[PDB]
Image (spheres, rainbow, N blue to C red):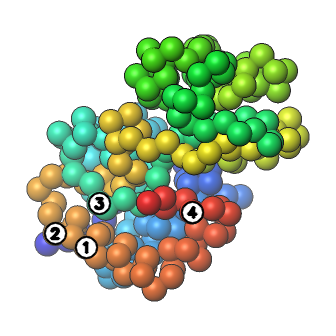
């Protein structure tokens, strides 16, 4: 059976997907997606705020029943837990000066100076595809210096998470004359297969319910209406 009340864990420090408003209500695209799915599942859902690092432990311990918290669908996590179908993409993407012909390809990037955050999934992607193939990829301790190096012309391009740069640098005055260069880069190995509802492996009925609700709210246009509140692009991806 479904939970009487599905307890859904999230970390409310990640706008525009999950945060708290002035009245202490949970808000964001993750919250809209969860609530809409729950409505169609005809189950009660209670949101539970905690730190992201505690979510999978809480799920395994049955303190909560589901995770919606921009949780990447990784093969490593798939070994321990289950996921719904993709909620939206969490891919990376290059940023360069407006008008730049740069593409996220080895051919385009040879001769270029690319910056990436040290220790990141973006760094790993850039390492295997670009740096070891001869592209000047330089790793940074701090994202802020990546962006100030880009605007100063020290860097030609920066490889970042797509949505975070879209909400951050590209909407700040310093990023006004900058733009994504080429399409997002997609690879489950480095970036996962999108985000999804995190679930216990044996709760197959609950997975079936979330997946059914998601398919239905996507095909009747509710997904796109909800996403448009936060995003002016195809956040779902491919």
Q: Residue, x 31% and y 61% (percent of image)?
A: 85
Q: Looking at the picture, tell me which residue is in the foreground, 98 or 232.
A: 98
x and y, in percent, of residue 199 in the image: 25, 54
Residue 71, percent from left and from top: 40, 46
Mark 2 or mark 4, whichever is nearer to me: 4
Of the image marks 4 and 1, the number of the one nearer the N terminus = 1
**Height in image: 122 above or below 81?**
above
Residue that mark 2 sits on = 205
State whether residue 90 appears in this view.
yes
Residue 230, quarter of the rendered image: bottom right
> CB of mark 2 within 8 Å of CB of mark 1?
yes
What residue is pinned by disc 4? 234
- Spatial distance from mark 2 to mark 1, Cα to Cα? 6 Å
Question: 117 or 94: nearer the eye?
Answer: 94
Q: Which residue position holds label 1? A: 209
Side of 175 where 110 appears, left or right:
left
Query: How far apart in space, not on screen, are marks 3 and 4 (Cα)?
Result: 19 Å
- Residue lying at 51% horizontally and 82% vertically, measured from the top left: 221
Which is closer to the viewer, label 2 or label 3? 3
Residue marked by disc 3? 84
């Amino acid at each position: 059976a479904l939970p009487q009340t599905v307890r859904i864990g999230t970390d409310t420090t990640y706008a525009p997907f999950s945060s708290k408003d002035a009245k202490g209500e949970f808000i964001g695209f993750d919250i809209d997606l969860g609530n809409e799915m729950c409505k169609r599942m005809q189950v009660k859902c209670t949101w539970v705020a905690s730190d992201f690092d505690a979510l999978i432990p809480s799920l395994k311990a049955k303190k909560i029943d589901a995770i919606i918290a921009s949780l990447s669908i990784t093969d490593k996590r798939q070994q321990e837990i289950a996921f719904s179908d993709k909620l939206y993409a969490a891919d990376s993407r290059l940023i360069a000066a407006k008008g730049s012909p740069i593409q996220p390809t080895l051919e385009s990037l040879k001769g270029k100076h690319v910056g990436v955050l040290q220790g990141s999934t973006q760094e790993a992607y850039a390492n295997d595809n670009w740096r070891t193939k001869g592209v000047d990829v330089v790793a940074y301790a701090n994202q802020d210096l990546i962006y100030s190096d880009l605007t100063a012309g020290r860097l030609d391009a920066a490889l970042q998470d797509e949505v975070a740069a879209s909400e951050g640098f590209l909407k700040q005055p310093a990023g006004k004359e900058y733009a994504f260069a080429g399409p997002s880069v997609k690879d489950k190995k480095y970036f996962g297969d999108g985000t999804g509802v995190g679930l216990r492996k044996d709760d197959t009925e609950l997975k079936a319910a979330f997946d059914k609700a998601l398919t239905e709210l996507r095909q009747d246009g509710t997904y796109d209406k909800m996403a448009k509140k936060y995003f002016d692009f195809n956040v779902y991806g491919d």
